[PDB]
Amino acid sequence: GSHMPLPIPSLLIAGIGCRRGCSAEHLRALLERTLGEHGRSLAELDALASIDGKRDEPGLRQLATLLERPVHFLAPAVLHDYEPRLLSPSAVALRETGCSSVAEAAALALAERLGGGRADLLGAKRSDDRASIALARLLTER
């Protein structure tokens, strides 16, 4: 009947924070690793998220093009809303942006905006010395 409950737009968002000049190839390898840890395929990603600001973002834009999937850059003030929910505070991120984890905050922020309900991180962000990636999913889950 019309009361048929459709739950999941099962959205999966990757939030990314990285050093200046980080390549699409580097970001993609780290993204693939992060997805693998959580038994997610790159095919399952809906969008990428990061922080907006004045630096140009060609690595992220190239990654979005490779994936044929969008990248959204969110206001620092928006990311700040998610401070209390972050798992992996970053001294560099905090100093530079006002946000304790760009990857974690951007993932949550975008998932909730596209999804219109609460999102949860799949886990703490995965990091190397040039980038960090976090995954967020729209939390159904009756």
Image (cartoon, grey):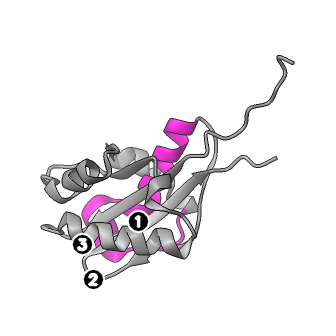
The residue drawn where x is 44% and y is 60% is 42
The mark that comes first in sequence, 3 or 2, is 3
Q: Name the mark on residue 73.
A: none
The amino acid at mark 3 is His
Distance (Cα) linking label 1 and label 3: 19 Å
Q: Secondary structure at mark 1?
A: loop
The overriding secondary structure of the stretch rendered in magenta is helix
Hey, what amino acid is under mark 2? Asp
**Dot placed on the residue nearer the N-terminal end, 2 or 1:** 1
- The residue carrying mark 3 is 26
- Label 2: which residue? 129
Amino acid type at mark 1: Ser
Foreground: disc 1 or disc 3? 3
Instruction: Name the secondary structure under disc 2.
Output: loop
Q: Which residue is at 38% across, 68% downward? A: 31
Q: Is residue 95 magenta?
A: yes
x%, y% of residue 45? Answer: 46, 53
Relative placement, left or right, of 137 versus 130 is right
**The N terminus: image quadrant:** top right
Q: Which residue is tagged 1?
A: 101
**Which residue: 38% across, 74% down?**
90
Crowd class of label 3 (few under 14; some 14 to 19; many from 20; radius 10 Å): few
